[PDB]
Image 1 (tube, rainbow over the protein chains, first blue to last red):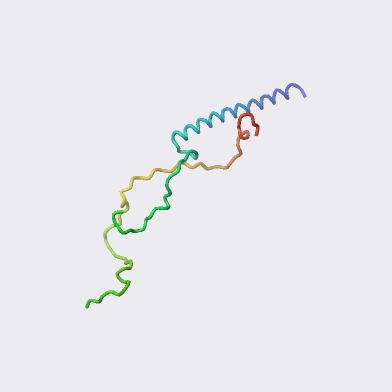
Image 2: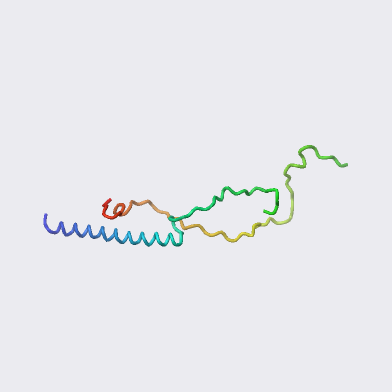
Length: 63
Length: 57
């Protein structure tokens, strides 16, 4: 087919691989930041459930 | 003119009228911390597949 086919295919491959490398580095940074200070979706460690707390009036008023 | 209460009368919940204001913060609670900023948006596919080493998809 000629040299331009291989040339532009190589350009497309290089663009894909460079984008993948940048995405992997960004993913590493995102994971590190979330694990250090969990405020995104990931690394959300559990917490006791709020809905299982009694709020009805009880025997002792000092609650 | 006093009448002794019947069985079950003193043991039921009664409403009561008062002019004392309702305490808005009885537990003296601090301000609750804000939740995480939940991310919204359409679920686009993964860019260039799984990006797991040499796997294309």
